[PDB]
Image 1 (cartoon, rainbow, N blue to C red):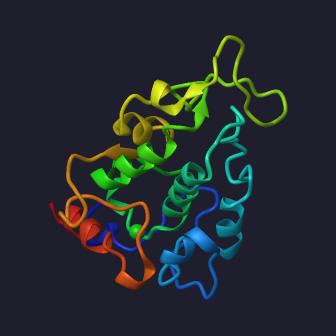
Image 2 (tube, rainbow, N blue to C red; image 1 turned 90 degrees about the vertical axis):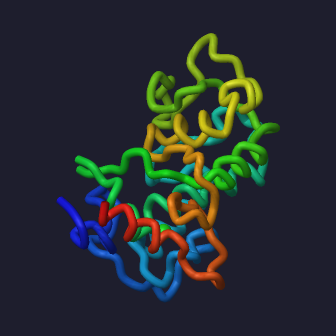
Amino acid sequence: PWGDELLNICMNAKHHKRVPSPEDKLYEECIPWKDNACCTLTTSWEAHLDVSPLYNFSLFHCGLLMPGCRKHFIQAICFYECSPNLGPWIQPGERVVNVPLCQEDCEEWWEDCRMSYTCKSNWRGGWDWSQGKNRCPKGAQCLPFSHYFPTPADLCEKTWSNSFKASPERRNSGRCLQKWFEPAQGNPNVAVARLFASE
Ligand SMILES: [Cl-]
């Protein structure tokens, strides 16, 4: 699996489009991808629900989640579900492993979530699942994100089960992806996927 075989594709996960294509309408935080998207309008909207049915995973498990924080998590979903530029990190259903996120992306996400609350530092398993929605298990204290995720890297990496890696590279280095970008400026991740598909 290699080279161009990896550019402009969508992972084989349950919601993804079979190939990327333009979308006339995508919802709010997913707008940057509408040029060429792996997500449908439906998915984009479902990404913005209080508890997205895409994963049935509640971010409000500790009640106190700041809007600035939740915004980052929604953008992360759009990135995951919409990006046509993840091919080089796709691995076997398919998924993504260690997509390198630029330092600013992890930094800002962390900074904006410091004041919000969670009860676990590893979200990949060990939840109480009685309502079809996850709850904090017995003994898991709700504390600030900065307690369970001491650093930006912890947050980037452990919330999404190693889909993302906190890159030491910065934005516009050509060596890391942004999880969100201003639509007007064009997709800076195209160049990065292209680079990694060659090596
Ligand atoms: Cl992208």
